[PDB]
Amino acid sequence: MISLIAALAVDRVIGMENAMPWNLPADLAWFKRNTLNKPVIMGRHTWESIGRPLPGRKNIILSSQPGTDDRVTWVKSVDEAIAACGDVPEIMVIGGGRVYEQFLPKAQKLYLTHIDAEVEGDTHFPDYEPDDWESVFSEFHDADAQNSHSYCFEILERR
Ligand SMILES: NC(=O)c1ccc[n+]([C@@H]2O[C@H](COP(=O)([O-])OP(=O)(O)OC[C@H]3O[C@@H](n4cnc5c(N)ncnc54)[C@H](OP(=O)(O)O)[C@@H]3O)[C@@H](O)[C@H]2O)c1
Ligand SMILES: Nc1nc(=O)c2nc(CNc3ccc(C(=O)N[C@@H](CCC(=O)O)C(=O)O)cc3)cnc2[nH]1
Ligand SMILES: [Mn+2]
Ligand SMILES: [Mn+2]
Ligand SMILES: [Mn+2]
Image 1 (cartoon, rainbow, N blue to C red):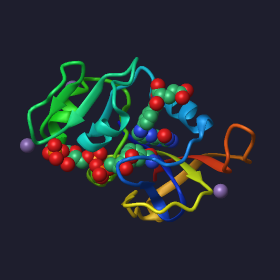
Image 2 (cartoon, rainbow, N blue to C red):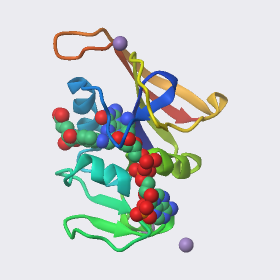
Image 3 (cartoon, helix red, strand yellow):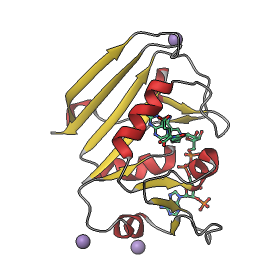
Image 4 (cartoon, rainbow, N blue to C red):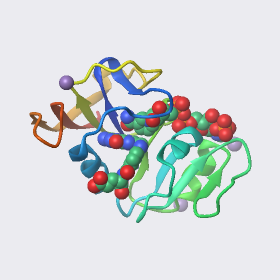
């Protein structure tokens, strides 16, 4: 099973200048809980944005060019990325925009955080078709001293 996880600001913005400009510790905690002990697939730009391997997860990087770091696994196509995960129950695709576009048709589940923040961005989460997806979990949180925007955790499953 393939799942996508992402945090979206208004208008599906997910990044700007190879960064995420907001800071929502509660959402990073949600990301860690839902990805720990699973393989994570990311594109090369997202690997450079994170800047280090994510501990406790098999890190698989898509790039058309040879890898430059043997602490992670480098693959050259979507099919190779999936194969490198082996026989696991759930593969987590962690972006960025180009990678999400390619894995969306193959995904059964989306873990989305909707952030009430207006962000100029240059990268968006794919338009998906709402009729294809059932919301099975949602949890709203107001802003607090640690998290400066309200946010909504949602899990959707392909109907
Ligand atoms: N809010 C969130 O949840 C979230 C999550 C992840 C990322 N982001 C943001 O998203 C942005 C980066 O996204 P992006 O769309 O620019 O880049 P990306 O999807 O992270 O990476 C694209 C790169 O991955 C490689 N790639 C993708 N598909 C491939 C394929 N089928 N075969 C081989 N290589 C493939 C290519 O690398 P080569 O050029 O080396 O071939 C391509 O240039 C940043 O702003 C980051 O902060 C946000
Ligand atoms: N909901 C969501 N939020 C994100 O921030 C996110 N980020 C990415 C890609 N970028 C990043 C950037 C930093 C870390 C990171 O530092 N993660 C630590 C945080 C642990 C914690 O804060 O409790 C980790 O071990 O996962 C992960 C992914 C992909 N999907 C996402 N999905
Ligand atoms: Mn092929
Ligand atoms: Mn197999
Ligand atoms: Mn806000």
